[PDB]
Length: 43
Length: 50
Image (cartoon, rainbow over all chains, first blue to last red; front, side, top):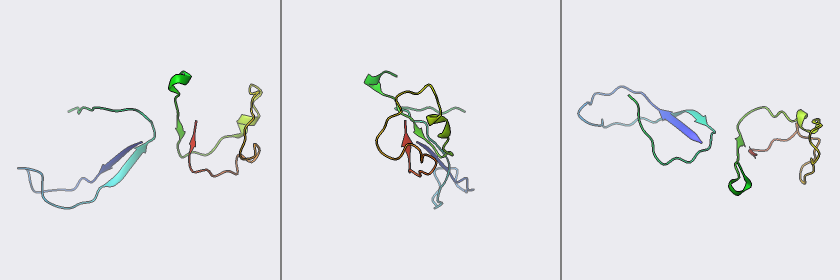
């Protein structure tokens, strides 16, 4: 299963990861089934 | 996939379509032990795997 969560809240810190609290709600779950070891990001 | 590495697929949330199973003439080995082979639309199992 592939679970995805996201919050997308505004912040005020750019120098580093901001200090604050905000829960993350799920978006979509994908019942695919696959062995995974690595991953990459695309700009 | 061959039997040495048997492959599986779990059925996600969808309306069961089982009327075409016992009605298929291609099947000739539809023998199994468990629930009745006729009350298929009245079953509410949590998760099903193939």
